[PDB]
Image (tube, rainbow, N blue to C red; front, side):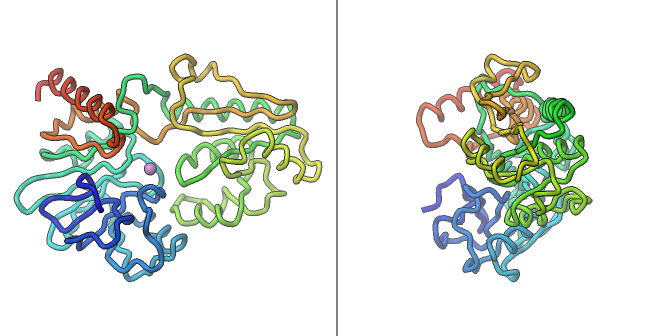
Length: 341
Ligand code: NI
């Protein structure tokens, strides 16, 4: 049974609600992005209308084989009428194809559903600037002040400088980057660009990347591992055992691996500056954990919400415990008292 925070009142609509069977009253199923916790339940046998971005719709058709007649892609930043209700899709600054949804209810209520997002000041000049929002369905993944991390630009600068240093010292080092979903593609694309290489990967991952509308992608990626000195591997193989095994397969081309694990936040963030980050090393293998986030930090979240001044907030993440829910409600009331709405 579908929970309340996935239903849009006054409509036939749900958001990211594919794992509950046929939801009573639902005439259109929105999907904010192509991450498994959100698409859970979609397959080629789905027969209701799915509304989403063009990029999400490429992935539904090619990766999950959803039939074309049930895929309804909408352009961003454009007023669209769906089943008699005005909606707008906005870039969420999450993974490729990720959106926020603005719903203009027939009674005059305006609702914003952020999906998963990384709040940015640039959102304060989208179509959000123009009008008031009564209800906010908020990605609260890192809704606590201990959650700090650097800008994505600082993290990419660290990774580029680390990779270029290592490979210039040893032209025989291979760079490996972990992945387990879409998102965070800048990590491996920025490193391959500094090294003058294409990124090498499995056929399954190449196919996924080919759905993302990234400009000049055929110039940047390949399935020919032998021609590439930046390889992608599943995240589960980014450990000393899995990397050793991989280096065996490379036919004595390389004698060292430098590997990156983009994580979200980790508690080493509460002590260490990005500049000061060091790897774990075993012999000729080094592994860096880098804090590349596609979700708001606490401070970014707070800034966005204080600017928007919603009347009510409904969290969509960390909702399963009373301690989580009570923590989040306390921060929402602080933010409202400090800003005066
Ligand atoms: Ni996500």
